Length: 141
Image (cartoon, rainbow, N blue to C red; front, side):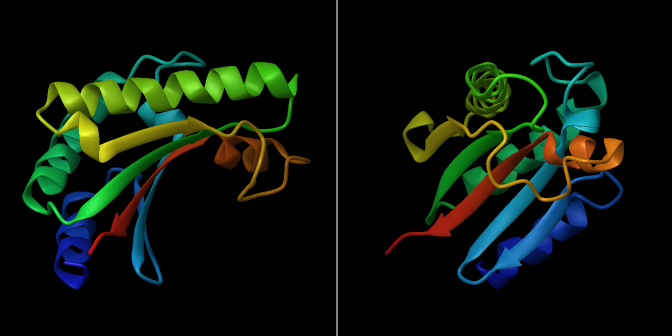
């Protein structure tokens, strides 16, 4: 890319529920919790294996960016516990991508718990939107 990978990602993620955002120099992929994970677990949902397979192929093909995997939660419960849970979910996505052949040295992962909500934690579907994993692709020189 950056334009080319973004267009390839938009095509592959069509109909998966994964959102693709152009964010200045960066590409951000929003993976909602309700379609990425089974229940409130950190196991990847059966239906999301093939979308992740496509993502891994894209990352392997476009080698000139870093891959930052960030887990998020809603604000219900303890901050420590949410950071824990969000870290677990980012771990699972990163572990899957590396199993598919993405160089582990290109990946970093964080849990952020309830920080940076994308919607209101006062409504049920707002809280559900905040439970997500984000993949940020940042260009390198």
